[PDB]
Amino acid sequence: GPHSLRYFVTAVSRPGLGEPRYMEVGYVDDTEFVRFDSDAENPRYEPRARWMEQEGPEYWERETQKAKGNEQSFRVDLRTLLGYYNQSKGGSHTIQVISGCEVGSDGRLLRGYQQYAYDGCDYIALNEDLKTWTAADMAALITKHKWEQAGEAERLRAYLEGTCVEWLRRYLKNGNATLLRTDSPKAHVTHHSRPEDKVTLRCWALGFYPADITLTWQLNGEELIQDMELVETRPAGDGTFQKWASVVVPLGKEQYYTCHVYHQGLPEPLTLRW
Amino acid sequence: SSIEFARL
Amino acid sequence: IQKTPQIQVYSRHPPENGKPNILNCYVTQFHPPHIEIQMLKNGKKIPKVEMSDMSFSKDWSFYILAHTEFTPTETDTYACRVKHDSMAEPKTVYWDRDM
Ligand SMILES: *[C@H]1O[C@H](CO)[C@@H](O)[C@H](O)[C@H]1NC(C)=O
Image 1 (tube, rainbow over the protein chains, first blue to last red):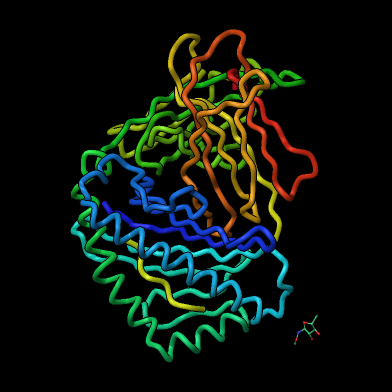
Image 2 (cartoon, rainbow over the protein chains, first blue to last red):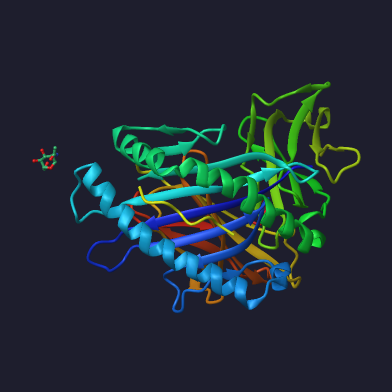
């Protein structure tokens, strides 16, 4: 199916404590594969996935340079925004960026994205056409005027359609054993007593990959997505994920509720009861 | 590899 | 905008005394990004704690994972202590192996 390459970029200022902290974390799908943290003793662009061992030393040097270049240039962006917003020179502020592309099974570009945010709010973003920008406020409108004059969209489109897409293909190729694997969810149900003859039934899906999964509770064939409690799918520390969904049912009437787990690792969805 | 970001 | 962090503590495998496992502490939906996260074994700070899976959601709030290797016991208790500007007192969430 489709695959993606994403970079989450963060720059956080801290007046009185030195230069802004800068971070770059990269992912291929739901798998972290590279990272750069300017607060590390010796700030290097370092691999986060074992298959990234296939990249020569030149790759690491180049990326480490590009990253340090960004750490400096974002220091400049933080000061600039202070001016756009007429803000105090002594407060902490945050610039966030999500950058990357998405490709289908055949390896062609499906989507490209470049999104910035300031202090947790939409600032500017490249539209799906990869030609025009959308500014969230008057401050971003200034940036928009500059980027249009510099042909920034064009430069970003060449990157998305060429560079971004090409490394994504290379990453999937080198890390196929990892990225293209499918770990099947292991499910089970726990039971918990509640006040007034009611019990909480919890369905757990463990050790699955990729992250996308669906957990639904049923009663006589119908779903209960309405009175169902759950948690956003989460990482378990070894490259796999887990999730749980719960529903409150009448005591003694547990056997009438079944859990359904759908995942691309389950040729047939699981169905459990307590 | 991430793109070289442009100034705001 | 200031969002309070959600704190989830859980293990990779269903807990089984004497069997290697992994303890996770997923801290999510917070803002600003400055935050201190500490995993604890019987009130004592765990040293080898790896941070990972940092990212943001659609609304830009931060997500981060702290995890470490551990082997369960019928005595040991684990917790995750978090300090964040949106909270007066540091918050501690204990691992519930019966969840
Ligand atoms: C913000 O900066 C100062 C302090 O609030 C104020 O005098 C000024 O009018 C504000 N913004 C502008 C337009 O300079």
